[PDB]
Image (cartoon, rainbow, N blue to C red):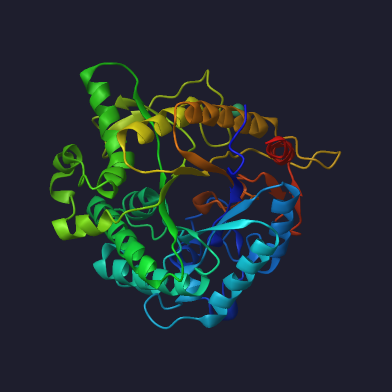
Length: 440
Ligand code: NA
């Protein structure tokens, strides 16, 4: 029933999703400014131009985290605020902003867990192919250096990237995230340059740091299960597992890219010399897992790569946008612990979206979200029992925000955001986490 006395308890956000103030204090244009301002890309016509106004209202965010009894806050720094041209001079006003925010967090007893890259590539870099270019890896590392030099006296726990599978595949293969390209080959190239940027950044950060750091990367992992034991469905499960999970885990673990996937991708695979693989495998202090759903896979020979489609289970619960499968969190952690070298581990996102409203009494009665937390935290207890070296849990999200291609329409917060007034209110699931955490 109990977590470690020193366990990290937080909630998570990303800069473009919450900050607003997109032109303020020298901020440059990101690929998500471009993409959200492109008609038709966002479901509901919204942008991150205002979002939660957390650029001005991070004090209110800190107020929520305190009310919840949290001891940590996962958030991202916007590259466009720091190096507005992407490769070029720094913007001291950007760094001063996050400096003040860091001091405010520490003053409140909240450990900052900083993500350097949460999808907001400076547009001038995208103009030169973005993650399709190796040069972008080099300048990511330079950005990482600058940030750690200024803030690494106070922040020990850093993640280079958030969810490179999204940035590469949704951004450059499927076209549903910024920058919105639709080419497999470019998606795969982007994956390699993201990974190379990660590895270069780790090295740069260790050199630039004023004290030893605890550096990780954050991956979205989706445990995958064949719908039957047929060779066709099992192979479809392996292909999906490789496309999402092992493509990133293996090179990070020093195992190269998975050979099955290299053979499957054929001519679309990127050109990956041994020197790049050595850099990609730069030793980490921790690994973050973002966990939402499983994939129950059936073979789908006529679909695009990886030729595997989800077989829905209507007896399972569904949220606004996903199937619920808490057991998958235990499965993927047990696999990491036993099969891969990363440790310790943090759950850097876990949460759900629902059609939340303010009820007549003023509260938000999101029982399904409460039950979602309760069920996933039970699986974490099981994983801890099995010896998994788990050191923290961050709910996605602290508050409702701009949820990428779904816009403001898809509410993941444990706090409700009124996007007209910018008032935040804690949901019932938030109060449950508060009281659960206080018990711990
Ligand atoms: Na439902």
